[PDB]
Amino acid sequence: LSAANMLYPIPPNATQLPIPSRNWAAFRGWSLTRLKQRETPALGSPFDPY
Amino acid sequence: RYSMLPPLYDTTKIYLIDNKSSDIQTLNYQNDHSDYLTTIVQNSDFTPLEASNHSIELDERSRWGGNLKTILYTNLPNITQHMFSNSFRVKMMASKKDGVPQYEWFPLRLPEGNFSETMVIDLMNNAIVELYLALGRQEGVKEEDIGVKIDTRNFSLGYDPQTQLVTPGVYTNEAMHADIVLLPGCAIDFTHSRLNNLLGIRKRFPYQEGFVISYEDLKGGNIPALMDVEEFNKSKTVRALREDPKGRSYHVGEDPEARENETAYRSWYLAYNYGDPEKGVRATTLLTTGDVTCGVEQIYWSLPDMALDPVTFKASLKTSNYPVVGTELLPLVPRSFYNAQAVYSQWIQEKTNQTHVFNRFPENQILVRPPAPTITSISENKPSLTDHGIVPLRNRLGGVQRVTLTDARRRSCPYVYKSLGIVTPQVLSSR
Amino acid sequence: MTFEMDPINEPTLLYVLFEVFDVARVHQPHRGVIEVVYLRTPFSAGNA
Amino acid sequence: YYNSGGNLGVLAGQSSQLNAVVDLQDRNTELSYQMLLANTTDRSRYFSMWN
Image 1 (cartoon, rainbow over the protein chains, first blue to last red):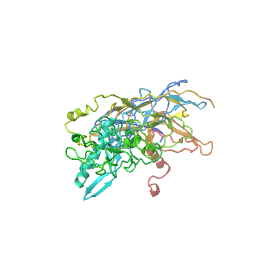
Image 2: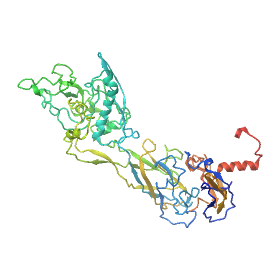
Image 3: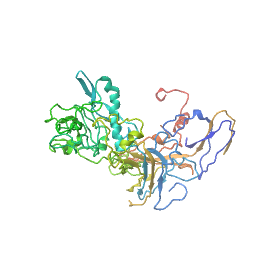
Image 4: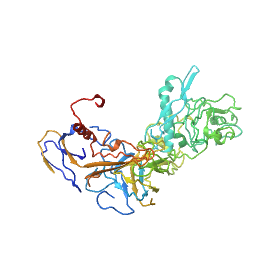
């Protein structure tokens, strides 16, 4: 895959969604989609109670 | 190297805060201030958690090794299930009908919170009472022959070497040091309790597991019976007091006064420096200071993903064998006071409180409330500021450190409120 | 970046993928010794 | 467990003691593996062993 995974919340009924970030170098390209919060388990923690 | 920005020369600082665990929401979503992960980055514009992949580089040519001046601060109660101070076994009588008694060991439990050495003693006997109020009085045993009872006063200050009775007619009301009174065929277990050190009773040879102390072991420490005061006109003397108000026999060994005047109440304090110091209790035990904290047990610190393996320690991933970097003493202190009110405040506390819980037997001179000893000592959680020695560092420190605080039995201490460290790395020697 | 999308009656997420170079070299000098060196550029270790 | 610093896997030589597995919750191994298979083989057949 070779890519940094980022996740930004999209409030219900929201239409616009800005995302600020900066790269000091040059990568390969962008790749994106859309997922449902309920269907996305919060990783990083050894357990998701919600 | 900080991967970005500009690198800095010698004498730098890498801080490991506990105020960073909330932001790392993903790693400490299960552990509370005992083994949480922190980000030793602190850039200031990259949102809470970030820089998990980035590593704080250190050169290949030379190894570092800075100090570690941590700031610990706990809030561990006096008594809790953790430190094994709430429970304490003690064989007490179960029944006694038609001369058909029995004795069985029962584990007791104490509530979380309450402190003070005097208050804990009253609680240890309060547990004895609730056991009786559930099994005792329903089966057969009376209120008189209640096995086990912690006291504090000396029961041989008024004793005269002629009559062999406490001439005052009342035991001297003035605590000296806590102990453990026992009745025929009943003791206390302290193999799995640290309450024994609280009383001030340690074995000379602590290395041997099993702190059993039966009634059979307390030979030559019989509590001298009182003198019948109301019957002193010229002659009487020899006649010890049997009953009293409400009628509660002291359980005399026999009717005679010769070799008998004594009762069936073996005392620990009397067995110590009044018994025979060759085959008595004073052979395996020791009269030590109370000390509320129960012990000077010292915690361990460690930082696996940063500090090198200290000599013989080995790498692994388990909260029960982390490479210790330096040990500190648990931030619990004794606070010496002075209550001249004592014993006199006892006579008043019975009115401050609505119900005599502890003092259910204000008549009996043995099953009463233990006289409040002078100078009460209480625990006080003081935020220590230790000074740890120099410790070598890795070749490439991680983005997300792991701050752990192991205990004596190698496990988490769920009573940590603050736990931050400061490290100031510096060059040692080249390769 | 500014993403304009259709409104949905439920919380969603914008899964982005900054394609980069996540490479790592493995060096084995002696018996029972593994030395690896990772390197993901851009985004070495987060952004700040 | 993957991409979780909380339960990062270990794989180092007993003598080295230096873990050779450095993971970041920023990476996504799971998805990565998926796409990988769909590029080297026909992701339509089944293979019980790997479920």
